[PDB]
Image (cartoon, rainbow over all chains, first blue to last red):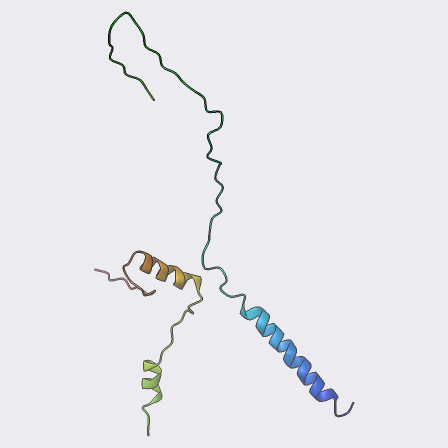
Amino acid sequence: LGRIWLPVLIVVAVAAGALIVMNVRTVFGSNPVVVTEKTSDNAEDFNPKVVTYEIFGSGSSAVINYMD
Amino acid sequence: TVVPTLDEVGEMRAVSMAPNDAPSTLAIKRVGQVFEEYDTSSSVMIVL
């Protein structure tokens, strides 16, 4: 391999250098924005508790104030 | 003789220090465009 050893080793070295270049070149940057995760709850109406107000008396009418 | 000296050419062909991939430059430009105020990434301070 007197006339084969040189070009093969040259190609091997060039491939190694290209691989190193490709790997490290992309590491820079790659983190421009930060996006926080979202964890919401299911907004549904199943078995809602029911509150009832009742006003009654011997009078005809009344004035009523209440808290919703 | 054809072109100016190297000093003038270097003065008129200067390159930005930070690449556009830089997250900080992108952040400043994003602030500028969102707030609709500017579109650069460099600022100076005037002291009185």
